[PDB]
Image: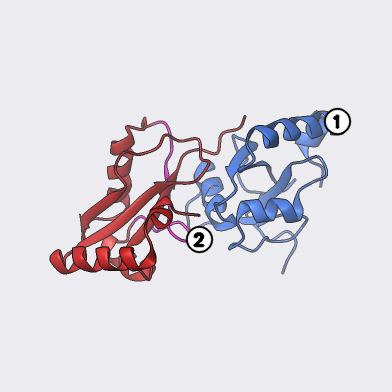
Chain colours: A red, B blue
């Protein structure tokens, strides 16, 4: 995926921003959230998240679902890098496993791969 | 294998359907998913998918697993042109590499390795 956050900020800028935020909040996970490019699902208003390291991926998934008010019947999927994060991991664990070199964790989301 | 999608639609019909959808959504790939004929695994409720080109094969595989609600403990094998597609390729790349001449990418799935040991 090609992230708008990276298109909007240079590596230098992002590297420093995450360094500042993490130093300030050592027990929180800084996450950049964007909808999969071209996906049909509605976009999201908030892109930057700073969550306690203990919440699970499943709980983070709920935060995103709530943010876009996606109906229970409609499925939502979280993507990190080239795979799907295991819902049981804590965001702190996902951060250590998948953090970008810039210090942020990048999570993409999408809905159902409906047709025409 | 014999694909029900092809049994139900002529080559002409299929070609036009994908042409229209690709023109409308250049950043999505039309995919047909069918269970390996005679396989034990449960059948799927949806056959046609329009997938964002940037998600990976591994991510799409998960979407299918969720569609049939198969416990992660049970195995799922995807096959394209009778081979397991490499999981790190994006669906867009898999499409360009393995798309049918009719414009659709055909993905088969089974609970057992049909074309492997």
Q: Is residue B33 rendered to the left or right of residue A14? A: right
Q: Position of residue B48 (x, y in %)?
A: 65, 36
Q: Which residue is mark 1?
A: B12
Q: Estimate how packed mark 2 is, as few (under 14), some (14 to 19) or many (20 or more) residues with alpha carbons within 10 Å.
A: some
**Label 1 lies in what chain?**
B
Residues under labels 2 and 1: Cα distance?
35 Å
Q: Secondary structure at mark 1?
A: helix
Q: Does the stretch in magenta take in A76?
A: yes
Q: Which residue is mark 2?
A: A82
Report the magenta residues as a range: A73-87
**Label 2 lies in what chain?**
A
Depicted A97 relative to depicted B26: above or below? below
| Magenta segment main secondary structure | loop
Q: Tell me the number on the disc at residue B67.
A: none
Q: Position of residue A88 (x, y in %)?
A: 33, 58
Q: Residue at x 74, y 61 (%)?
A: B83
Q: Residue at x 15, y 64 (%)?
A: A25
């Amino acid at each position: 995926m090609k992230w708008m956050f990276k298109e909007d900020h240079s590596l230098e800028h992002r590297c420093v921003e995450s360094a500042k935020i993490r130093a300030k909040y050592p027990d929180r996970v800084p996450v950049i959230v964007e909808k999969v490019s071209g996906s049909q699902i509605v976009d999201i208003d908030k892109r930057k998240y700073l969550v306690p390291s203990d919440i699970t991926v499943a709980q983070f998934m709920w935060i995103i679902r709530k943010r876009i008010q996606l109906p229970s019947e409609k499925a939502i999927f979280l993507f990190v890098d080239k795979t799907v994060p295991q819902s049981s991991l804590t965001m702190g664990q996902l951060y250590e496993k998948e953090k970008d070199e810039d210090g942020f964790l990048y999570v993409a989301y999408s809905g159902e791969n409906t047709f025409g």
